């Protein structure tokens, strides 16, 4: 129930605003900046602001705060969803998220904002549909929005029907300083870049534990994702009835399904860190990394970030494999490795001095995280069975998909 | 080639499930 | 060697706060790496960058040894950088200036005048209790020097040492003797400042320093006669700092003596008419002369002239002039109080002025001008100002009104009514410390209790969110329950107090969310005292006390448990400890 | 500038008019009061260019309230545009008509609203519904006179499922702003029709459809079972707001659900994966998810019994997110994960956030008080925190120890010696008063209690009212228990708090203590040093009446604020 | 800008 | 004496800072922030005089950057304004057409001039030509 949504700047100047209900005066945006400054200075800053009886919910964007003033107790979740959709639409239309594009495409920006929502109720949410009706460089509204099938525009013609899938794996490991991993969750991501002719209805099929149990084939390696979320085009009725993933694929790259379940397997990388820091004399970095993944898998672009001292200077690195660079902006040493074969064991020995003057205040102990990304590895063991590509005209599709394993929340608590 | 796992051909459905 | 200009340009090129912080961190890391290698060639650029980062708001704890090393260096630029680092990032609380004592002592005998002056300035700016003890002898040695450019620095160092070490002023008694004939303006000003500081530190030197009054008068007359000069002549005033120092010395010299006041009476009279206040310097000189005349035993004509000047400056539309006039009137409150009564209209108008400082000065003048005859008349004006005052002045206005009522209240009934009105209107603006004072004043007064009790009962039932008003009402109820309700033991005719509304109000206050544990405790104490004070509502508060004994608060739970135990086992002894507390000033 | 712009706008060149419009928009967007040029732009309004029409409409909407008198020259243009063949033009005109805050402007637009009510275009139908809702909000009496309620009710029973959802949202807004008289409640056939169109509704349409079900009150288990089965597929939607709306609808339906039936168990089982997925949402929605979980935790706490690992605050989690996670863990604290909670609190106690550290200490104390099985573990953690040598940490540990002693002091005598010498130089009133109360109540395991109280008696008359009262109570307790070593201390305390203490409550307490001491010292042990009963801790759970109301109010601003919907709106 | 301007304009 | 004298811009950026009273770094930063907030939230008709924390907080900016001082309540208010004007004139003479940009580049020179002019919060150079000559001689030393 936001009264009006506006785009602000880092200096407090509003890049663009669009009133939807008119129940709140436009001058309330000025008081938002002092309120935000006070909240940040007092630790009471929150995304949902409140200026008296009018709430100005703001979201920190790439360059400006997306302030959405509201008057009544409207759907806060709905307002957040509308703001996220607007951000996604702006990112799709404008490749840059800064003040340069805010003041460069205002003519089309105003039309897009007007078409997006009216009277506080969002109406248009398809980026492709918005581009087919609002362009920066007008015809009647497309019938796809009026029709039920708003996730697959009809009439698409392509020379070849190629779909690029991406099996993105996110391994998040929360290892405490005591050596025990508390939060070990793996989140799947089934994103497909479908580029074909027409609006084929995808018939997803994979080696799911629930599907195998229902079909009686619950004896092989079946992925039992704790949380699986279907895309907009995915038909939830088939999934609820018999796990039938039947939906119209979108024109382009989209995330159809995203698995999310806990992980009970050993970590892909076992990192042992040693802090031989003298009392204002020297610092020791006994970093040992062990690759617990299969030797047949190589972690490309491995970056294990080891936080160095805030006031540390004159550091010397004694490692075996992988370049180590101390970033003054990062104030930490990142164990950069180009390719990390599975089972590799890297030992590092840091040595640097410390200032004679003691620090006035403590800086905390940020966790140590790695940036490993080993593709072509399916740790979960979930294997896609088939993709039912059905077209009324009839064509032979050649879909493609790649499994990518990366390091997500693989943060290890510091000692 | 491409980093992060090469693209592989996908089937249409489980042929063993009828 | 990154130049300071390059660092400034890079900082200006950064827009995001995070980007600026990252750039500052990179620069600090580079500076620390350079310092760790013991670099001595480009140390000036590193010192400048570190100073800029510290001024920008960046930590510089590690950059303390480099400044100390550069302080003991030989390059003039390096010495200046070290002195600047010691002055900026070096302090007595830092404790890193202890090692600088040897460097200062070594540089104390340096032949270069700039190095010695820089060291003296750094010592004065960063004066420490222990540094002055080990450097007191060096300061006195340079005080007898004939260097005009160094005389001011020596005087400043001596003044800083005296301020930091008041017991070290005894060693400067003979060093400044026979130093009133300095031709240089700076040396004479330093000598006058040192004499004023010595006189203010202790009064033993007032008699010794009062002998130079004729010399100071002659110097002031000569300066007034020499009204034109290329140096120190700004805005038509030649040596305004020297004139201000002379006026301050005259005001502070002989403040309680007749000979000193009589000696400078002619000089003050000449200055009061030979000075033009068209410019800021002239107005400041006139204000200083008026303050000196008021603070000294000046003649009746001098006081009249000062009053006329203050009145003329009050009508000035300048905000600074109005503030100066208000400050002078506040300072001359006790002195010439009758003559200050002619500006009552101006004081009242200053409360409505659009200047926060001007409004505060007017309010202070009105508070200080309240007498035993205008208190009743000024009460309405004070109430109006408090009702329509700023949030930062509402509490101050209420405190001033309460102080005036407690100091020069025309009557107990009028003072009690004013206090009740202030409590009702102050709400959350009444200070909590004033609650004990109000309680003591209520306890002292034993003649107006029925009307006061009725007013407190009426105000408590209306609102209870006012912590000071609520506490005052609870204390009044506990003190005079026997007088608030008469014949309330059993059912009677409908009156203000029925013996049951007070108990319900106390229970609601105790259980109300608007309790800070202080008003709740006062309400519990009043309820406990009402067991013997009031004999109408009995056998019902015991259940509440027993239930109230399990409160979450340890103190509140203990108080409730003690009350329940007293009610259940010391019913006959309840009245043995319910005697009224004594009343004392 | 202004004159040149007016001359350009008064020209017959289309490129010049477009340039002038762009310049005016840039000035208006840049913060230039272009309302004075609204009458000049009024003449240059009827333009064939679609881009120019949108800019003119935006300027009129932004210059309508500023110049209501000058807005009377746009009714003819709006009427002419209301019959535009292009659906986009008609939708823009409908949006502009409702956006004009003119009292006399909506009166002349009633006929165009009636004409566009039956628009065949689903976008046109949605625009007409939005305009009708805007007119009703601006003028409820005008909307009632126009009789759009009958058209709005039949709108849901039509095609254009997104248009149906828009009409349903408009009708709910009208009834939400209505005083509840003449409600638009529908029979089960309407619910079934909405459920049939629920699968064809968009992300915005799904939320609107789920909002309608929030007001209907189910009366049959079979109808409730069908509604739950229909809402179950909504949990597999990427829309977090749609997920939140579905969760709220399921919670509302569970109020009339029967625990004996297996439908409630299936709904509870399917809700946990949804909560886990929602917890991994964006930081802006993370706070909303935490608030929703806290609101639903008091209703069905057994739903998230096994959800504890996700309750840990992430390193990159925001301060508000960390506070919400800590609150969820405290509300979700259980003996099964007591060790994990203690470890997380110890991990949370090493952060650099002073407010975060205080919140962690308070949560640890609350967990220790709620569950007595970890009382020894809580005491050990408090001792470790005190030994950590943190001023704020020391104060928090002292407060926690004082709270635990008042709650479970039967086995709290072993920490008096450790807490006796714990850098008691802290002048924090909360820590000082807690230490004084602990010493007074636990003046049995410490042989130097009088010596410790001697240091705090130097400034008893000027320490604080609460601090002074606590010190007086401790002195009285020590005298009652061991008066041989505190006979003079009690007299000194009575003299200081009776003669040098001007506080009314403090003076009364001192006088009462002196009277009790002078009356019967033996009776003071049974009166002052009595065995207090169990301390009634305040329950943090919301009232059942408020909990039921908050269940319906799911996703509103009041859920985040934890306040009633009528207590937060103006 | 406003920074390159003289503080006193002299 | 002047407890602290600092030069701050209108936007809040501080171009100068010189405190004659030893205070904690966090306390000094908080005091500077409070002074900036008071000055940044003050009108043009406030008399340029504020009694904050019992200190004569006199604010008087002749350009975009403002100037503030804090002295005890023992002397005339116009004396502080006259001293500030004299210091500004001396800095302008030493530099020549002093601007905000030049202030950042000449921070060390400005600090040296301020130290040579006022030491310990008290006036050290009453004359205007003598201080300029001394500063020029010190600069020519190297």
Image (cartoon, rainbow, N blue to C red):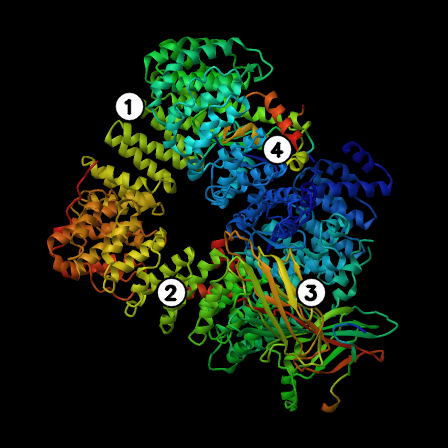
Q: Which mark is residue F110?
A: 4
Percent position of residue C201, x then y: 37, 27
Marks 3 & 1 on one chain: no
Mark 2 highlights which residue? Answer: D383
Identify the residue shown where x is 32% and y is 12%.
Answer: C258
Report how far apart the C-alphas of labels 4 and 3 lie in the structure: 69 Å
Residue labelled with disc 1:
C372
> Same chain for marks 2 and 3?
yes
Of residue C331 and residue C468, the one placed in the foreground of this image is C331
* In the image, residue D433 above or below residue C352: below
Q: Is residue D38 left or right of residue D49?
A: left
Where disc 4 sits, the SS reads helix
Q: Residues within 10 Å of mark 1 (few under 14, many from 20)?
A: few
Identify the residue under disc 3. Answer: D162
Task: Tell me the crowding category of disc 3: few under 14, some 14 to 19, or many 20 or more residues within 10 angstroms, Cα based.
Answer: many
Q: Position of residue D39 (x, y in %)?
A: 74, 37
Q: CA distance from mark 1 to mark 4?
A: 55 Å
Q: Percent position (x, y) of residue C21? A: 62, 50
**Residue at disc 1, secondary structure:** loop
Viewer-proximal residue among C363 and D209: C363
Q: CA distance from mark 3 to mark 1?
A: 80 Å
* Discs 2 and 1 lie in a common subunit: no
Element at badge 2?
A: helix
Write down the chain letter for disc 2.
D
Marks 4, 3: nearer the viewer: 4
Which of the two residues, A47 or A140, is positioned nearer the viewer here? A47
Screen quadrant of the C terminus of chain F: top right
């Amino acid at each position: 129930s936001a009264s009006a949504v506006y785009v602000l700047d880092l200096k407090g100047k509003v890049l663009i605003c669009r009133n939807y209900r008119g129940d709140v005066d436009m001058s309330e945006v000025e008081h938002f900046m002092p309120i935000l400054m006070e909240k940040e200075e007092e630790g009471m800053l929150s995304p949902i602001l409140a200026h008296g009886g009018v709430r100005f919910m703001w979201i920190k964007h790439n360059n400006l705060y997306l302030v959405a003033t509201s008057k009544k107790n409207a759907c806060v979740s709905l307002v957040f969803s509308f703001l996220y959709k607007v951000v996604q639409v702006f990112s799709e239309y404008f490749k840059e998220l800064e003040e340069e594009s805010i003041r460069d495409n205002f003519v089309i920006i105003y039309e897009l904002l007007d078409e997006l929502m009216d009277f506080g109720y969002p109406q248009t949410t398809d980026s492709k549909i918005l581009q087919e009706y609002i362009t920066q460089e007008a015809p009647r509204p497309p019938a796809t929005v009026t029709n039920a099938v708003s996730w697959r525009s009809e009439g698409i013609k392509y020379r070849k029907n190629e779909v690029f899938l991406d099996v993105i794996e996110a391994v998040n490991l929360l290892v405490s300083a005591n050596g025990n991993v508390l939060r070990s969750e793996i989140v799947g991501s089934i994103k497909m870049r479908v580029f074909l002719s027409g609006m084929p209805e995808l018939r997803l099929g994979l080696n799911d534990k629930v599907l195998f149990d229902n079909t009686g084939r619950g004896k092989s390696k079946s992925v039992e994702l704790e949380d699986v979320k279907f895309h907009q085009c995915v038909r939830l009725s088939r999934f609820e009835n018999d796990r039938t993933i039947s939906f119209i694929p979108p024109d382009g790259e989209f995330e159809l399904m995203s698995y999310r379940l806990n992980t009970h397997v050993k970590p892909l990388i076992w990192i042992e860190s040693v802090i031989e820091k003298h009392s204002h004399s020297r610092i020791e970095y006994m970093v040992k990394a062990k690759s617990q993944f299969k030797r047949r898998s190589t972690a490309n672009n491995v970056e294990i970030h080891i936080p160095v001292p805030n006031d540390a200077d004159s550091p010397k690195f004694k490692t075996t494999v992988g370049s180590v660079k101390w970033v003054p902006e990062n104030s930490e040493i990142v164990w950069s490795v180009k390719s990390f074969p599975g089972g590799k064991e890297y030992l590092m020995r840091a040595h640097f001095g410390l200032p004679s003057v003691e620090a006035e205040d403590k800086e905390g102990k940020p966790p140590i995280s790695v940036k490993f990304e080993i593709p072509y590895f399916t740790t979960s063991g979930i294997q896609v069975r088939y993709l039912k590509i059905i077209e009324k005209s009839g064509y032979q599709a050649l879909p493609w998909v790649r499994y990518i394993t990366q390091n997500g929340d693989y943060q290890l608590r510091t000692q | 080639d491409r980093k992060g796992g090469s693209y592989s051909q996908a089937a249409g459905s489980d042929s063993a499930q009828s | 060697p990154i130049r300071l200009r390059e660092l400034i340009r890079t900082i200006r090129t950064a827009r995001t706060q995070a980007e600026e912080r990252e750039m500052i961190q990179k620069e600090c890391a580079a500076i620390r790496s350079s310092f760790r290698e013991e670099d001595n060639t480009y140390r000036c650029r590193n010192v400048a960058k570190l100073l800029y980062m510290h001024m920008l708001g960046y930590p510089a704890h590690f950059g303390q040894l480099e400044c100390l090393k550069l302080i003991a260096s030989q390059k003039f630029t390096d010495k200046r950088i070290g002195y600047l680092g010691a002055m900026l990032l070096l302090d007595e609380r830092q404790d890193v200036h202890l090692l600088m004592t040897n460097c200062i002592k070594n540089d104390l005998n340096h032949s270069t005048q700039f190095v010695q002056g820089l060291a003296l300035c750094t010592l004065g700016c960063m004066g420490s209790s222990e540094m002055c003890r080990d450097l007191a002898g060096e300061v006195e040695k340079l005080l007898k020097t004939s260097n005009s450019y160094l005389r001011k620095k020596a005087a400043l160092c001596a003044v800083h040492v005296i301020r930091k070490v008041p017991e070290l002023m005894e060693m400067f008694l003979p060093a400044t003797k026979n130093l009133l004939n300095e031709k240089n303006h700076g040396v004479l000003h330093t000598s006058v400042v040192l004499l004023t500081e010595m006189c203010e530190r202790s009064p033993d030197m007032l008699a010794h320093f009062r002998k130079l009054v004729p010399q100071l008068v002659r110097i002031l007359k000569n300066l007034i006669m020499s009204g034109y000069s290329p140096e120190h002549d700004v805005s038509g005033i030649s040596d305004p700092f020297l004139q201000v120092r002379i006026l301050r010395l005259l005001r502070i010299l002989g403040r309680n003596d007749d000979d000193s006041s009589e000696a400078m009476n002619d000089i003050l009279a000449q200055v009061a008419t030979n000075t033009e206040t068209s410019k800021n310097v002239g107005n400041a000189i006139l204000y200083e002369t008026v303050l000196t005349i008021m603070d000294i035993k000046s003649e009746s004509g001098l006081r009249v002239l000062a009053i006329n000047i203050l009145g003329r400056f009050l009508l000035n539309n300048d905000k600074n002039i109005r503030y100066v006039a208000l400050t002078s009137l506040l300072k001359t409150v006790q002195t010439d109080h009758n003559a200050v009564q002619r500006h009552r209209s101006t004081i009242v108008d200053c409360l409505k002025d659009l200047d926060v400082s001007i409004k505060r000065r007017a309010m202070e003048l009105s508070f200080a001008l309240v007498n035993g005859n205008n208190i009743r008349g000024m009460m309405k004006e004070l109430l109006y100002f408090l009702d329509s005052c700023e949030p930062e002045f509402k509490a101050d206005c209420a405190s001033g009104i309460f102080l005036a009522a407690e100091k020069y209240a025309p009557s107990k009934r009028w003072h009690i009514d004013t206090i009740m009105r202030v409590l009702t209107t102050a709400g959350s603006y009444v200070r909590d410390d004033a609650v004990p004072n109000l309680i003591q004043l209520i306890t002292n007064s034993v003649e107006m209790h029925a009307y006061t009790v009725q007013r407190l009962y009426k105000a408590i039932l209306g609102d209870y969110s006012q912590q000071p008003l609520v506490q005052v009402a609870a204390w009044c109820i506990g003190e005079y329950g026997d007088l608030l309700v008469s014949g309330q033991c059993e059912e009677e005719e409908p009156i203000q107090v029925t013996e049951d509304e007070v108990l319900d109000i106390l229970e609601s206050v105790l259980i109300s969310n608007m309790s800070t544990s202080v008003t709740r405790g006062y309400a519990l104490t009043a309820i406990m005292k009402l067991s013997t004070r009031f004999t109408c509502t009995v056998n019902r508060i015991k259940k509440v006390v027993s239930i109230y004994g399990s409160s979450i608060d340890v103190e509140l739970q203990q108080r409730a448990v003690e009350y329940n135990a007293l009610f259940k086992k010391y019913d006959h002894m309840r009245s043995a400890l319910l005697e009224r507390m004594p009343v004392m000033e | 500038e202004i004159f040149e712009l007016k001359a350009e706008l008064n020209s017959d060149k289309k490129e010049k008019k477009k340039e002038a419009v762009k310049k005016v928009i840039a000035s208006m967007t840049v913060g230039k009061d272009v309302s004075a040029l609204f009458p000049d732009v009024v003449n240059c309004m009827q333009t064939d260019n679609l881009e120019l029409k949108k800019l003119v409409y935006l300027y009129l909407m932004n210059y309508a309230k500023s110049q209501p008198d000058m807005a009377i020259m746009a009714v003819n243009t709006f009427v002419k545009d209301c019959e535009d063949p292009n659906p986009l033009i008609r939708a823009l005109a409908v949006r502009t008509m409702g956006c004009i805050r003119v009292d006399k402007i909506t009166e002349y637009l009633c006929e165009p609203l009636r004409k566009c009510l039956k628009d065949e275009d689903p976008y046109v139908r949605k625009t007409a519904a939005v305009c009708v809702a805007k007119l009703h909000d601006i003028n409820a009496q005008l909307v009632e006179d126009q009789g759009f309620l009958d058209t709005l009710k039949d709108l849901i029973s039509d095609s254009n499922p997104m248009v149906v959802a828009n009409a349903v949202a408009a009708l709910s807004e009208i009834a939400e702003s209505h005083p509840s008289s003449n409600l638009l409640d529908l029979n089960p056939q309407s619910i079934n029709k909405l459920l049939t169109a629920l699968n064809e509704c968009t992300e915005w349409g799904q939320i609107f459809i789920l909002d309608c079900l929030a007001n209907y009150m189910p009366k049959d288990d079979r109808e409730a079972q069908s509604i739950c089965e229909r809402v179950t597929p909504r949990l597999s939607h990427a829309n977090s707001a749609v997920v939140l709306s579905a969760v709220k609808v399921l919670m509302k339906f569970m109020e009339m659900l029967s625990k004996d039936l297996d439908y409630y168990g299936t709904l509870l089982k399917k809700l946990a994966p949804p909560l886990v997925t929602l917890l991994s949402a964006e930081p802006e929605l993370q706070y909303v998810a935490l608030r929703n979980i806290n609101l639903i935790v008091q209703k069905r706490p057994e739903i998230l019994k096994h959800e504890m690992k996700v309750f840990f605050v992430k390193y990159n989690d925001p301060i508000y997110v960390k506070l919400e996670k800590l609150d969820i863990m405290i509300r979700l604290a259980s003996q099964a994960n007591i060790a994990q909670v203690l470890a997380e609190l110890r991990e949370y106690a090493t952060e650099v956030d002073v407010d975060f550290v205080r919140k962690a200490v308070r949560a640890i104390g609350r967990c220790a008080i709620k569950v007595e099985q970890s009382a020894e573990r809580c005491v050990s953690t408090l001792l470790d925190l005190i030994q950590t040598k943190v001023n704020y940490v020391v104060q928090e540990a002292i407060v926690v120890i004082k709270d635990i002693f008042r709650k479970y002091p039967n086995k709290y005598e072993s920490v008096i010696a450790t807490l006796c010498e714990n850098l008691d130089s802290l002048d924090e009133p909360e820590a000082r008063a807690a230490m004084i109360w602990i010493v007074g109540e636990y003046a049995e395991r410490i042989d130097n209690a009088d010596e410790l109280l001697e240091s705090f008696l130097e400034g008893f008359h000027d320490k604080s009212t609460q601090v002074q009262l606590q010190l007086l109570t401790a002195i009285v307790k020590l005298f009652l228990k061991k008066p041989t070593e505190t006979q003079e201390l009690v007299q000194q305390v009575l003299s200081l708090a009776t003669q040098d203490s001007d506080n009314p409550d403090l003076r009364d307490r001192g006088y009462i203590y002196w009277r009790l001491l002078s009356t019967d010292p033996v009776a003071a042990k049974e009166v002052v040093l009595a065995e207090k009963p169990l301390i009634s801790e305040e329950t943090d759970l919301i009232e059942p009446t408020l909990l039921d109301e908050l269940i319906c109010y799911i996703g509103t601003l009041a859920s985040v604020y934890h306040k009633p919907p009528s207590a937060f709106v103006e | 800008k406003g920074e390159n301007t003289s503080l006193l304009h002299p | 004496m002047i407890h602290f004298i600092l030069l701050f811009s209108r936007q809040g950026k501080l171009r100068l800072q010189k405190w004659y009273i030893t205070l904690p770094d966090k306390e000094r930063k908080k005091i500077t922030r409070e002074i900036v907030q008071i000055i940044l939230s003050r009108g043009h008709r406030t008399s340029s005089f504020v009694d904050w924390k019992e200190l004569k907080l006199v604010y008087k900016r002749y350009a975009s950057l403002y100037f503030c001082c804090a002295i005890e309540n023992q002397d005339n208010e116009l004396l502080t304004l006259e001293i500030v004007h004299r210091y500004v004139e001396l800095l302008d003479k030493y530099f020549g057409n002093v601007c905000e940009l030049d202030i950042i580049f000449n921070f060390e020179k400005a600090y040296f001039i301020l130290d040579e002019f006022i030491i310990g919060g008290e006036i050290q150079e009453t004359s205007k030509k003598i201080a300029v000559k001394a500063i020029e001689d010190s600069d020519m030393l190297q």
